[PDB]
Image (tube, rainbow, N blue to C red):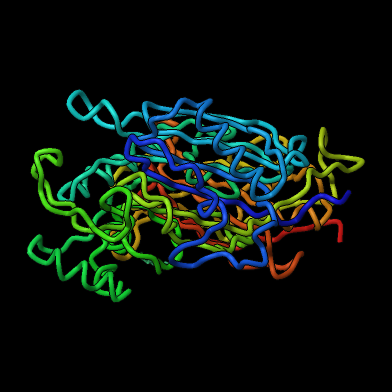
Amino acid sequence: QPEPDMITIFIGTWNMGNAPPPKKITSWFLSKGQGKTRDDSADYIPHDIYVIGTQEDPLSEKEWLEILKHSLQEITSVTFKTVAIHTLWNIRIVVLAKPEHENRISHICTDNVKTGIANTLGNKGAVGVSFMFNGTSLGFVNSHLTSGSEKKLRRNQNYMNILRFLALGDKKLSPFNITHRFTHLFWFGDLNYRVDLPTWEAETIIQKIKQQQYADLLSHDQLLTERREQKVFLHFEEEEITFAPTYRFERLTRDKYAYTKQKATGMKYNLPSWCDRVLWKSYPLVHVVCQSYGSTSDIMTSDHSPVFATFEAGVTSQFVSKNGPGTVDSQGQIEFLRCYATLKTKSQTKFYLEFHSSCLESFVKSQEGENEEGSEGELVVKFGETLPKLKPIISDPEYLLDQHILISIKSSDSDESYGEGCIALRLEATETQLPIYTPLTHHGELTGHFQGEIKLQTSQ
Ligand SMILES: c1ccc(NC[C@@H]2CCNC2)nc1
């Protein structure tokens, strides 16, 4: 049986509003309702991996696992295997996979982050799961961020705390947060960003939703506007939204948005909003295609509607040669020419690089670069032709061209990363000098750039 080069992944996010689900939730897993929906001809085809994120989930892990597995069984006639389940308070993630994948999945990690201090520590945060699927790392984060139209800055702070402190993936990648540890990272949940229009406009907003005219509402969606201004989710993607706002509904119908201030809302308005979202970030030049993004219309136990997203995701096989793993393939090398880092830091320390990749036996430390002053104020750290020659474990170009190099630029004084980025080895040519580029981030904020040239030698 050949190993796959593609898999399909289902992502669901549902704020269940502390209520048990209805008896049938199959529309969710079938990507049926409003938005970008899945073709009827695919209904019997199982996804490879189903990742279910809930918020305000009132069920025990056992109760929810039984509903999920039963649902998938009814749709597909496949008994899914549980990869992982992790719950923080009422925030939960479930990962289910087809039984044929059981021995393709390894290195399963789970973690949680609690957001806020004192007052604000008590029910918001994130859960996550990572694992390897053959040669591909996959990470999944379900977050329930701070509620309320006037707390977008809190939400952005919650996001930064989650991507700093959630401990998933390979712990040897010590300079790197979850935004660099995975071939494919999916981040979803009740992100709680709102449509930021005046309260008085509530009935007008409802009118626009009934006409399926979302453009003037999405232009005021706080997640899109905060993303635009590089305040949150830098370098993440989201598929175009073509479904009605998923919050806040009257229960047991979808005919009514419940937006008016009530004692039960802390006297806050809940204008109709896209609270419930799926975003992703994949390494450069890896195949990832969103094939559905929408909301269900027939699941009405909560004041939110479930959201679905599905993806085609490129995967690679575990590689064994006569040489690596356990030695170098002398036929392989990665050389960096004319490289320099441009940093936003005001500090004056020396910097060195670390190169991390699963194509190396272990990470590689460079010599210190030479600091110069940029024309517009900046620190430029020059490496020239001084960077070490990297010695991959396998030289086969069908392996090596699928790999990536993670780069950290570190202070010599503190050994603290000032910036992290990623370079694809999916080059237009081998044995040829070609431009390379990555932005550098730290704690998910832009801190600079790394650019230069690469020269990759493979066995071909
Ligand atoms: C908010 C922020 C950005 C954005 N598109 C630009 C990205 C550039 C790389 N892919 C899309 N859209 C909304």
The part of the image, by quadrant, that contains residue 411 is: top left
Which residue: 45% across, 60% down?
A: 237
Examine the rendered structure and indicate whether residue 321 appears above or below residue 459: above
Tag count in the figure?
Answer: 0
Q: Position of residue 143 (x, y in %)?
A: 38, 40
Q: Position of residue 45 (x, y in %)?
A: 70, 56
Examine the rendered structure and indicate whether residue 118 appears above or below residue 360: above
Which residue: 27% across, 45% down?
A: 155
Taking the image as drawn, is residue 334 in sight?
yes
Q: Is residue 129 left or right of residue 228?
A: right
Which residue: 60% across, 63% down?
A: 453
Q: Position of residue 279 (x, y in %)?
A: 45, 54
Q: Quadrant of the C terminus?
A: bottom right
Q: Nearer the viewer, residue 389 or 386?
A: 389
Q: Nearer the viewer, residue 354 or 201?
A: 201
The part of the image, by quadrant, that contains residue 39 is: bottom right
Q: Is residue 251 left or right of residue 52?
A: left
